[PDB]
Image (cartoon, rainbow over all chains, first blue to last red; front, side, top):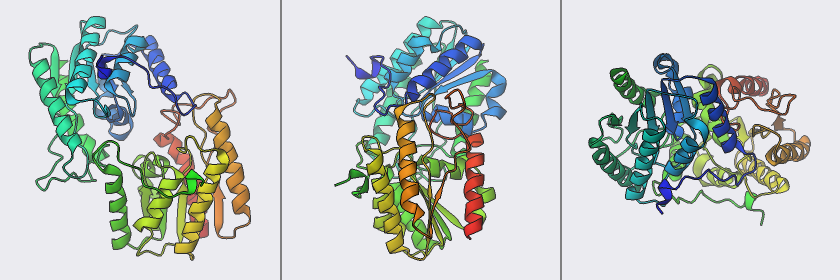
Length: 212
Length: 212
């Protein structure tokens, strides 16, 4: 099987159960709330809630944020199949995941993203799906930049025929002309600072407002 | 050997070199700046820069923040031995690390923390050292809470005889009476929200101001 599309939870190898606690909180959120937009993905989604304001942009759209740091595509797929899409009927589901899929080829990661879009199209067929491109990472040129670019080319080609599936390249140009990423935009060359989040969130908010 | 006290870098198994890029940025920071306080540890240190304001409290003390998400004690020890203490002469070094030392016993983690204090006492003998207790984690009672408590008891006993070594329990009581941690304080039951950071930062700032 493609490991990126075989749904599985993140196994607890530490002992505090925190990943399942997070998923269960999100299942209870979907049980108790009626969002128009649900966001799901990895830390780039999760820390937007905190580390961008979120409140200025996305709160007024009636949104839930199911980002979890460290998730790969198959973990997001499992969470969507195991309660986080129940009891709700969102207009838009925003997906941002794949940069953590270490050991999967770009084609495998793309298959994971396609499986997520297909699951959302089955369980929540009224919703449009937005998929964000994977951002560049690392301070200098490196294989994960090339991998993430290739995922983005394959995902964009896969969604091009798909009316209510929308690919969004939210990258304002974080890789400069000298090949570097600034720590002012990504403090550890992966995770966005508040400054890094501003252009990303504005691009995503403009698209969401269009679609809504 | 105790693996917690054997200095080693975090090996890059992903391919973007981001951990070494972070360490090299901190080495360049120590080369170019003259801090009075340097903070080093794991994400609980790192995200205080962002996710608490930091600017209100710690910026005026002339501080560098060398936190890196995911580091264990042996990684902080290696970074301190491999350039992050050069060219500087701080008054205080703040250490907060050990919650990520999975697979090490509490006694081993305590040995890692003692090795960090000893290295700082050799390389920067004028500095006082502040060690923060490891915080509770997980939504409900679990073995890592007990482990972290035991580390804190052993570290506090180790530092008690040590004039300019200071143990700080910065926990305002995150574990409630029903055994839970709220996601309002730790959004993923490990990492602090802005709200979680407030009491921690105030306790640490009060001690730093005393000592300074």
